[PDB]
Length: 51
Length: 53
Image 1 (cartoon, helix red, strand yellow):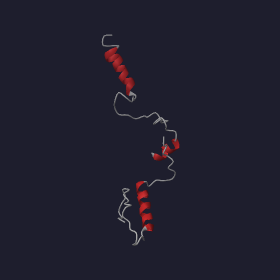
Image 2 (tube, rainbow over the protein chains, first blue to last red):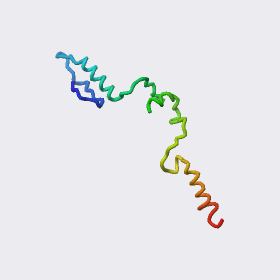
Image 3 (spheres, rainbow over the protein chains, first blue to last red):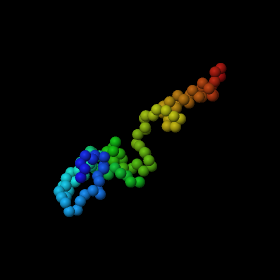
Image 4 (tube, rainbow over the protein chains, first blue to last red):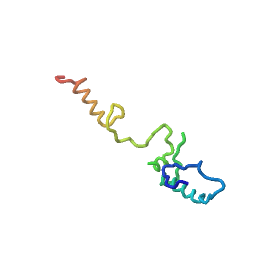
């Protein structure tokens, strides 16, 4: 499932259905590292003020 | 920058900063302390109290 993406580029239309999905744990690591790289500062991000 | 504005939580009328915005570079828009200097030049040097007044 690719690997080196840190620009919030996660392809969701290329998995597979009968072969190995022994990457769902690895997907979680890939998802987590993308989130950490984009915003490496998260303690209480209520600062949206949607209005 | 993000963390400080979080404690604000009241920015609804755009900026509404509690400071005085003590920085600016140029333009007849936002006014620095040079407005007073600009005013006296216009009032004295060229508009009201001209030379030989």
